View (cartoon, rainbow, N blue to C red):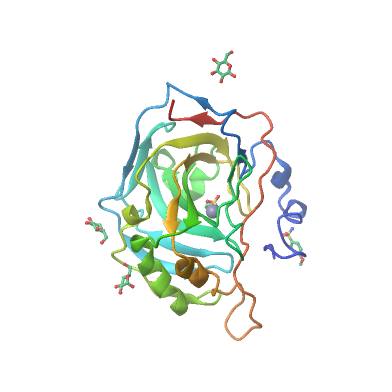
Length: 257
Ligand SMILES: COc1ccc(S(N)(=O)=O)cc1
Ligand SMILES: COc1ccc(S(N)(=O)=O)cc1
Ligand SMILES: OC[C@H]1O[C@@H](O)[C@H](O)[C@@H](O)[C@@H]1O
Ligand SMILES: OC[C@H]1O[C@@H](O)[C@H](O)[C@@H](O)[C@@H]1O
Ligand SMILES: OC[C@H]1O[C@H](O)[C@H](O)[C@@H](O)[C@@H]1O
Ligand SMILES: [Zn+2]
């Protein structure tokens, strides 16, 4: 099965997912000097006040905090997006050490971790149909750097001991994802893909420029999770990030002048 190790990591994925070498793969390095301000971008609207979180799951690659997406409870609109995109889940990618962990990089800088808030375009009815479309998904990416603690992350941190191994889940109701945002919504945007198999080229990426700060203790608890299932030899869930992929025939646009 695909993973992040030497024998099943990103350099192997193309053998079962040939789109891994495609024209629109993610993540990418964001060259800030090359990225151009785009006056055609509309204001970005993150509308999470009615979000309904349900559950947190260790899926063997990361942990997903899942939302009720049966209605427009928590949506992303505006910016580069045409129409309404509905929040389905968020997850993170992180490193074994503070100096790596993000998927996107900024002028080749790697952050300690990266948060992905995943949304699907409601014109396509369901996530499964959305991932058949070139504008099916919008992922809001947020970098994490290590410094002061992020208070709105602590509830996530504290439940991780209950989902240590692959396949474990726990109730995770009444979690407010607004507490994971930075102050500014300045962003870069480009067309890309899922960063894990099946690597589908369906994503409008919106990557915020301002990182959030989390404490060393918070990210250390991410690193206590396990890739393995219960009873199996312990493999710490660390370095679950894909490196930057070729930009090819793309441009990164900036929301800010
Ligand atoms: C059993 O060994 C493997 C190795 C690689 C992969 S892949 N292509 O990364 O999904 C799958 C299985
Ligand atoms: C299968 O669903 C997904 C959704 C999102 C992502 S990512 N890591 O945000 O690009 C990967 C896989
Ligand atoms: O409990 C987390 C969040 O859930 C939402 O459905 C509520 O409308 C918010 O007021 C609350 O902060
Ligand atoms: O032909 C000029 C155009 O080139 C494109 O590649 C850029 O995205 C536009 O911002 C520019 O106006
Ligand atoms: O908000 C997410 C979770 O945070 C804490 O774990 C609370 O104890 C729990 O009730 C809640 O579901
Ligand atoms: Zn991701």
